[PDB]
Length: 56
Length: 56
Image (cartoon, rainbow over all chains, first blue to last red; front, side, top):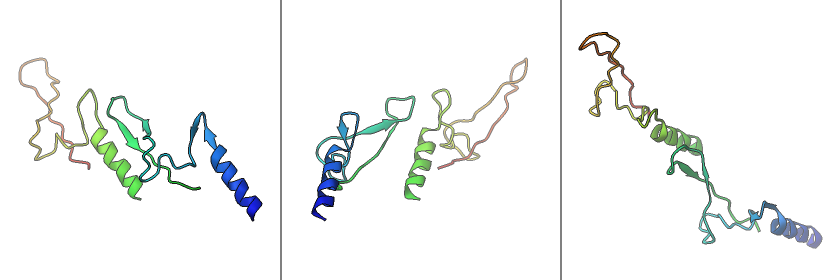
């Protein structure tokens, strides 16, 4: 179980898309790191909220 | 379901055609915004009404 949880932590540290990291919870419910948006509109204000909690 | 309804609200608040929103119900039966007329006649005063209700 120690080995498996070490593998889980390794994955959480390395699981990434491009240079950003996701599983660290940098965009959690109350994460102070930064904020992300997927703009899906032809207007500068048209974008919505996406969140990813902390799963360490 | 809440996420889906939030998408519905985003569509309603963002649905527009030529910098004019449509799903807001600006052309409803009792709408106070304005009356939409499409002139199809070759003379004066042949306006044609179109009605779209609020879709929030």
